[PDB]
Length: 116
Image (cartoon, rainbow, N blue to C red; front, side, top):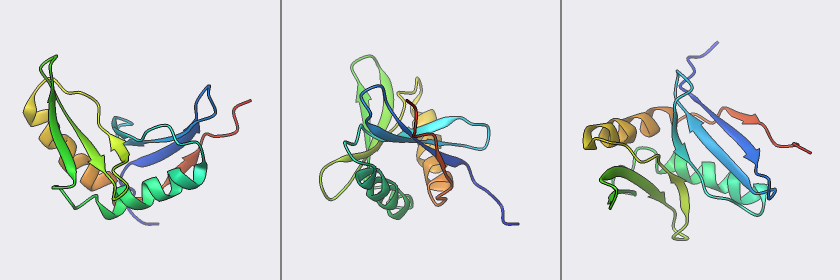
């Protein structure tokens, strides 16, 4: 077999909204897409995060007024294809860039959808 680098999990929310979370080797969620009305938007969501995974500049390195460093990966459609969790330190945001770059080159999607 081949070496795995993290995994995506496509789950639909309580409002049936399709949202995949990117997790690292320890299951640490490093990226989380927005609520998509269709799974087709989530397929193009992961297609875009995988293509913009080495594109460090496409990540929006921002700091919340809570003093929290995070990054939102944009699409051509101005859509957040993956917002990161708000970190305490800036170095944790940079490790986040490296981690989403590492595990974002994968496409190992776990279908958690079908919750009814």
